[PDB]
Length: 377
Image (cartoon, rainbow, N blue to C red):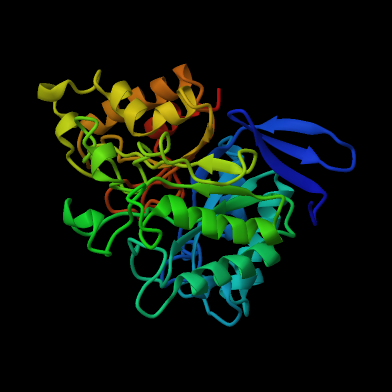
């Protein structure tokens, strides 16, 4: 049942941590941030050219976060891959460590701070988010075998809560071709080769065999199937990893107590959606849009829903509407008890969103953080 003595499960729409020996159960909330870099060709979380890695973890904790989503790529979790771009004067205890060793060191230190870790298979290779969980040179079997290896190793760390199976399933063409051309993810189309709802079951089953105590986080797609997507006026305008409209009629076939749906959602800094125009009702139109794309998965169906990525520049060198957008989203999350989330990102080096840290990798954006802090109390 568990190699750590700790077992994670969902009961209703809440995540619990169970100590299997004592029988003690505690509901947990995830007040999270994404710290990315292991999925990039740096092969290590970013910022270690400017900061000490432990200081970073301490700072994250000091802000009241208790969870980190950690993107990785295939090579970052294999022995022998060397990190690039670390200032070893500020990080002397990382000298001579490969990427995998640094990942273990970070997760252990997070655990010491009571910080939960969600592992996110973010890129197959270190360059770009593929739309599917396989490529020409890298098969679904390869992808699954990588998850198995990761689950066996990291399943031993008590604070690792589970697996975000694939970052942002999406499409690289427009409907109608996106549903049939084999280049992008679908949901409820019926073809198990492209249907993310079916692949997630296959990948999830394999992971739970070796890490039965983990949770399986399943993101949305961009498009699902034409019947579902056409059933709503903004059906073709969901984010990558953000379309959960097909969950109702095409649920992922995995145990209810292990499954967490994990939509991504973004504001005008990422894309100028038509619905961000005051002409189309911005921002009072937003709750119904969020509700349709993903919110109903919790509010109507009662699944656990954890927002896996959301963020924006909050008016710092971006679209000023982003301030209104992030405020409205936080208001809505509070009102509707979406208490579990991972903000994108801790890193400032995200082109279209910036992060919680400013470009100096040291000082935070006080206003952006103050808004976020409302979710943590």
